[PDB]
Length: 105
Image (cartoon, rainbow, N blue to C red; front, side):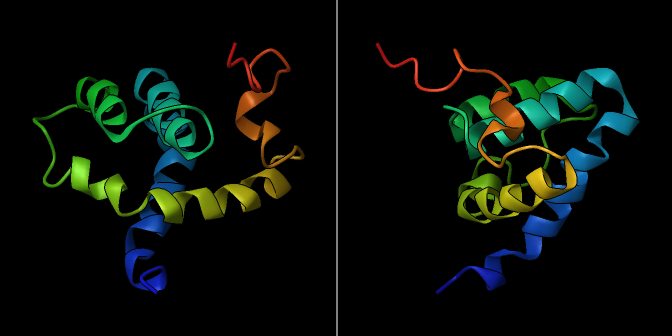
């Protein structure tokens, strides 16, 4: 498969969202929101590329859409580890609520 080969960005993403709260509150909440969002929450690359684009300083970064597009399945993996280091559940790590579970209807 193409997991490890694409995991090259996984690490960066993990630390990016983990330390993203250090650089600042704005970009922080956003980074984690988008990242963790498309990971478990209902989010799309485009949307994750929008807020981020206006969240991170400087002009659009090189390969944004195609970035998480091939790392989506790689980011949803580390999420299972975050919960262990967050003292919470892997699916509740981001949700942290009931109403925000499966409100399809």
